[PDB]
Amino acid sequence: DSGTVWGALGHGINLNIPNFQMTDDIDEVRWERGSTLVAEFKRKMKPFLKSGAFEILANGDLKIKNLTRDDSGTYNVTVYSTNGTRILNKALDLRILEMVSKPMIYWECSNATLTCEVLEGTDVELKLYQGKEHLRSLRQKTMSYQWTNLRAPFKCKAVNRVSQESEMEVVNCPE
Amino acid sequence: DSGTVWGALGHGINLNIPNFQMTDDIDEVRWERGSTLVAEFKRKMKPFLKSGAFEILANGDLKIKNLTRDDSGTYNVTVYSTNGTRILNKALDLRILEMVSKPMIYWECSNATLTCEVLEGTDVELKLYQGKEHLRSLRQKTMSYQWTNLRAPFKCKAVNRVSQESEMEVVNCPE
């Protein structure tokens, strides 16, 4: 059956076979992304790998080395015992995202407005905190908040499923 | 005899047997943690590994795949020749740490105070530099320094045995 996995572009990920345990009676495990065999492990063989991009691990997990936009999609694992029987057939959804960069915080004293902004990343949420209160969150790469007090630093955190990065600044206005 | 080894949480580590070389004259090498045999290599036999977390390498090194706060402690290696002589018995201290995150630098012009702060890490030391002079070090995740001049940018470095991460900012106060 299908679950969801999130990976970061240009990094590795390990697709692990759901609620499984490996054992000496397992003759085969094969991984197909969509309808393409990507890797196949057969107990007594050096494995079949589509390319150098994939590697089949000791316990049958698919290890993709450096994710590419062509690697996302529905993967399928089917594993067979020695008496050739299909033990399992499960499906996973690989979705890949881009990592976030460190946020920038800048401000404008006249309108008392602070802006937090980030350059890198995908499906980014930007979170603002001042001291220990969470001020605002937005799924945007740029966010502006009009302050009420300046008793504490502001913290801006940029986050997505695959990364997190934060910044702090004190609004330091001419008075 | 004994040594210390440092590993990062959620990463792998190889505990190598100091100044040893594997030859056909070695019959056995065993690795123990507390009252458990974690892994054992014995000559005409198949390896004993306590669970899937460990793997015993070709040369007898212990490979722990994904460090967990519970994996730290004294590990013992004992290796034996084919004629039953205990060739070696060495002890190693596995200390596992959390990797440092990138420091955030923010500054307050009124009291001319700069603050360097880091969110992630364990056994962290913060190191402050302005230009080429080392300003201050503190074994804390937050450090504050009141400046004298602003002719150079500040650089704050967060470091611990298993990681290091730096940042730079130019204090830019209104006149």
Image (tube, coloured by chain):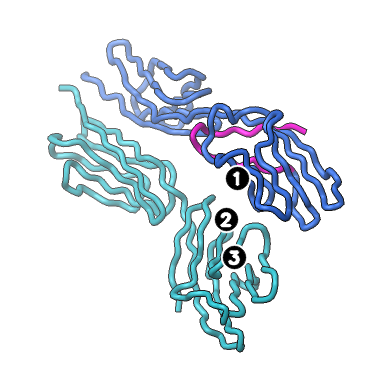
Chain colours: A blue, B cyan
Residue that sits furthest to the top in the current view? A111
| Residue A48 falls in image quadrant | top right
Task: Tell me the chain of label 2.
Answer: B
Residues B99 and A24: in front is A24
Q: Residue at x 40, y 16 (%)?
A: A144
On whether disc 1 and disc 2 are found on a single subunit, the reply is no
Residue type, label 2: Lys
Please identify, in this view, whether the residue under mark 3 or under mark 2 is nearer the observer: 3
Circle 3 residue: B56
The residues bearing labels 3 and 1 have C-alpha atoms spaced at a distance of 20 Å
Q: Position of residue A90 (x, y in %)?
A: 76, 37
Residue type, label 1: Glu
Asked if residue A20 lies left or right of residue B36, the reply is right
For residue A9: magenta?
yes
Circle 1 residue: A55
Q: Residue at x 42, y 18 (%)?
A: A142
Q: Is residue A95 above or below residue B122?
A: above
Q: Is residue B110 above or below residue B155?
A: above
Asked if residue A170 lies left or right of residue A50, the reply is left
On whether disc 3 and disc 1 are found on a single subunit, the reply is no
The residues bearing labels 1 and 2 have C-alpha atoms spaced at a distance of 16 Å
